[PDB]
Amino acid sequence: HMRVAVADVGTNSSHLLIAEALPGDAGGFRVIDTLKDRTRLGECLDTRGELTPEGEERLASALTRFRELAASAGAGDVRVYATSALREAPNGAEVAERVRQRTGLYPAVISGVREGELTYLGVREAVELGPDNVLLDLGGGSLEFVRGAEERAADVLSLPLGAIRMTRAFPEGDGKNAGRDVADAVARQVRELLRPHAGRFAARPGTQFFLSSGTAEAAADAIAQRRGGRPAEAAGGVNGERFTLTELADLLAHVARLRPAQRARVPGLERRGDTILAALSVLHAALDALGAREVTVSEGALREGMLIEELAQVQTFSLALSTRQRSVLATAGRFGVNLSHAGQVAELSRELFDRLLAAGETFPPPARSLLTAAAVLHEAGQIVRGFGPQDIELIAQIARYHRKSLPKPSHPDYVALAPADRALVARLAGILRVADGLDRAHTGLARVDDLRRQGQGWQLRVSGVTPLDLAGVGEKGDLWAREFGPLSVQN
Ligand SMILES: [Mg+2]
Image (cartoon, rainbow, N blue to C red):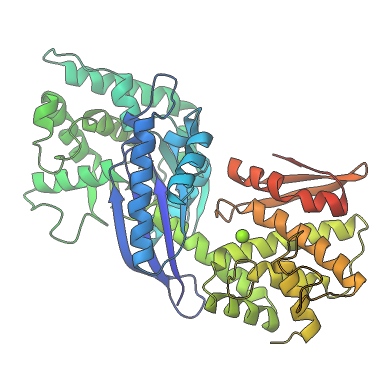
């Protein structure tokens, strides 16, 4: 069964999940392995918010450990999403490309809203959600608020209220009440930024509140040990633990009275003494402003959401395919290709093909089928079932197109298709290269919004793309330009 590796790069730490899909095409997975790396990019940002070469080194090291664990488990490629620290760094795009060059993995920045939607799915995989749920996810950089029902987020708000960010924003003095003063000021900042949107996430009869990520997990462990319990490692973690806003307030008042070095010795807060005071003030102030009385902590988060969405995309693509095209996908899988990438390239290829047809481009009847198959097979190294021998030669020549044919036209075994077929191969290859460029970062997120004639050329509007995707289209769209005319890409 399919083995998949997903990872997220946050502000305090990075996380990897390796899992195997469950039989029945039902969108489920079994966990194989998990890893956390204390990357702490938020402590590697200069005054303008740029990630330093030290943070780049810590990023590359995390992604190298991740890539080795995935390879060690047969997972193959690792999809990597990145949140607040890379998102906000003026040099974020340049840093992500440099890290790809050093590790092979590309940390693709996602929006706060998509971060929230995916985190909620991970929470859904770990704890019991009801008809009306509010999730708070506090990281080092940002705080997401998410409201939804039993299956997915309906509303997401992202605010710059992260724990690292707030610790650095409100430097602590050395007085007796210096801790309380930090806690009060952080809470005022929380209310100031949350007041205009709080109604969207406020408690109503029956609302359940949930918390994810490291601060909340540390708070749950520390609160349970204050109730008389053992360290969270017994009971298998803190997943599904509940605590009250009163227990949180009491933990916060205790932390506030201690100096930073004593905070590291509070049970359950041992690995978070430096940011924990501001982090607990954020959670208390935000929950209090929404009227929450009790929370449930979830160990599921962003990486579990990425896995669900990836399996969902793959299995939805596979389900709607014809029997013949499904056998191509199974063949490609046996060739060890990445099925998430192949499905996305084929869906993007169909989208571009269909718009060209709408704008009056002419194609022969089997063109869409040939393009789909070559899109699924494009990364099979072995090959450079419902298809006749001509169609399979066409597919192979589309999948491995080059301007200089590896075998010279005079070389024995050179395969010279008829002129109409030569023309078809290049046009469809030109589409396939543009689609491949749109999933260069392996995010599965790109979408075609519009494709229109622009003089003797074309204008393409896309969403869900990274800087790496946009550059891929520029580099690989030369063939499109030679066959369809100049192509400009937007958004
Ligand atoms: Mg590709």
